[PDB]
Image 1: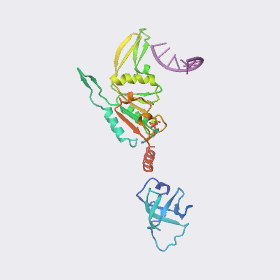
Image 2: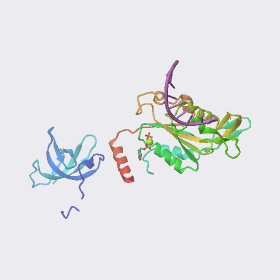
Image 3: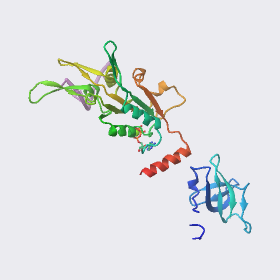
Image 4: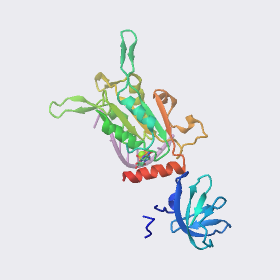
Length: 86
Length: 201
DNA sequence: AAAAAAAAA
Ligand SMILES: Nc1ncnc2c1ncn2[C@@H]1O[C@H](COP(=O)(O)OP(=O)(O)OP(=O)(O)O)[C@@H](O)[C@H]1O
Ligand SMILES: [Mg+2]
C-alpha cells in the first residue's frame, strides 16, 4: 500500500533459475539449522550475504524482523550478495 | 516456432525438403539426389513432434510407424479386381510417396525382416516385385527420415556409439547425417524451456 | 495372396 512501492518485489522461490540480476525481497531474517543467516518466504528460503551490506541507520536489526533486502543472486552456490537492508 | 533449440536440425530439415539435383549419366548410371536424416536420442526430446511438423509442412509425405507396418505390403500387394476378375498390383507405402518424403517412427522397434525392404529401396531407389507371374520394376525416389531410440532407456555418453544403436552398420552407412540429442540437466536451460512451454499452453 | 494365432525346436 506504500506510495513509493507501486519497485515490485519477487518471491524467494522465483530466484532459482536466474542469476547476475538484482532483486528486491522481504522475509523473516533468522538463523537456519546449520547456523547461517537466511530469509524465509511462504514460497521458499535462500542464504544471505552480509560482508558488504550497508544498512539504513536508526533501525535495530534483530533476528525475527521483516527486512527489505536488495542484492544480486549467484548460482555458483546459493548466496544472495546484499548491498543494502532497510 | 514452438520447438526450443534444435537449430541445426531445423537447418538440415530445410536443406532436406529442397535437396540437391539428381545426376544421370549414359555410362555412370544413376547418382542419388536427395538427403536422408536419422535422429536418435533419449525419450522426450521432441523428435516425433518435429517429424509431425515435417509431415504437415511437406508438399507430399506419408506417415508410417515401425511396428504397425509389414514390408511385404509396404511396397506392393497383389489383389484381385472385383469387376474384371484378374489380379493387379497395388502401390505400397512409399510407392505412393514417389518423389516425396517418408517419415517413420519407432524405426529401431520395427521387425528386422521388413528392414530388408529399406535395404532394397534406399540402395537404388527402385523396388522390383516378382510374384504370381508379375514382373515389373517400380520407381520410388523418396527420401526417408527416421527417429529411433537407443537400446538402453537413456543414451550412455561413456559408451561406444555402435553398441548404443540397435541398427546394423549397413543401413547406418547410407544415412547422410546422424544426430544425437540428450536432455542435459541445467537449471538455466530448465528455466528457459519451462517458461517457453508455459507460454505455449 | 496376405494377416494373425499356436505348439514345438
Ligand atoms: N524443445 C522443446 N520445445 C517444446 N516442447 C518440447 C521440447 N522438447 C520436448 N518437448 C515436448 O516433449 C513432449 C514429448 O513429445 P514426443 O513424444 O513427440 O517427443 P519425443 O522426443 O519424440 O519422444 P519419444 O522418443 O518418446 O517418441 C511434447 O509434448 C513436446 O512438446
Ligand atoms: Mg515422442
